[PDB]
Length: 282
Ligand SMILES: Nc1ncnc2c1ncn2[C@@H]1O[C@H](COP(=O)(O)OP(=O)(O)OP(=O)(O)O)[C@@H](O)[C@H]1O
Image 1 (cartoon, helix red, strand yellow):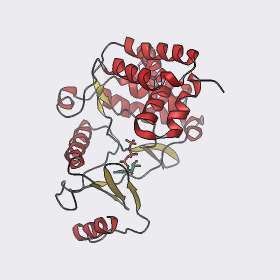
Image 2 (tube, rainbow, N blue to C red):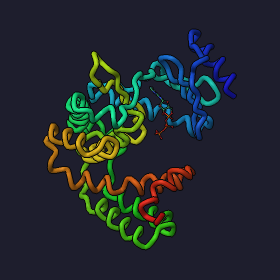
Image 3 (cartoon, rainbow, N blue to C red):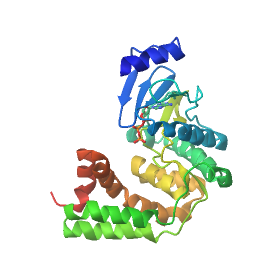
Image 4 (cartoon, protein in one colour):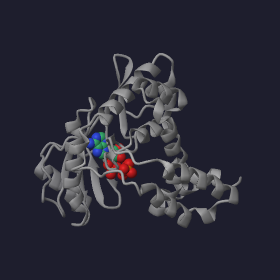
């Protein structure tokens, strides 16, 4: 298909260096990752419904004014190609490695980069956001607990199951919070940094697919899991978010299970395996 798509690209946009260009033909969409541009070509006219969803989420996130880059639609959604396509800006930068982020000369700067994005997300107009993004539903964690029990419990030791029931229950115990923007995979590989005059700057965030109106604690949990307690303590102290710790820990207690349940439900053996490692024996 992909030498069709390429002519379509050269047809729609003459100048587009396709040597060096990466390619992900995952489940629903083919993505051409070019120099300064990304092209998403859905497979099936069903999956093409996602293109205006992605425009709507990126436009809503852009309007919050986070102070960091988010992918920009460079084109309207087009009915060209097999089922349509969307061109987005490519964001430049590299994920921050744990070791790169905790050195004593950078940790305050790194904390403040996370804090200023988290602060702007917590201060978003959620009335505007609730019209476009998904919203945290009070039933989410009961839901997740059901699927963990259905799918992973039979694979666990009895001690595994008892640990998981406690972690699931701490999540189900949390009351319902929907007061800001939540990215939902913060401190992943989709958070991009650059050296700006020899110090880290958080320049871009890609992958707004899981974004919603939700709990500010959920993104803080992910920063902690990725970068360790020293860094998340600094971000929390800057945010004045000391009251969130029990919520933060409840999110974090569900991350190994989230891994495992998505490994199964999607079909990655290494994920499914590695989640469960603490819910079995050597
Ligand atoms: N506008 C962009 N700027 C920078 N990198 C981008 C951009 N769009 C896509 N990418 C990169 O190319 C990849 C294309 O895959 P896609 O966006 O479908 O994500 P995925 O990794 O499959 O999904 P997920 O991380 O949500 O499970 C992304 O993972 C990201 O690294």
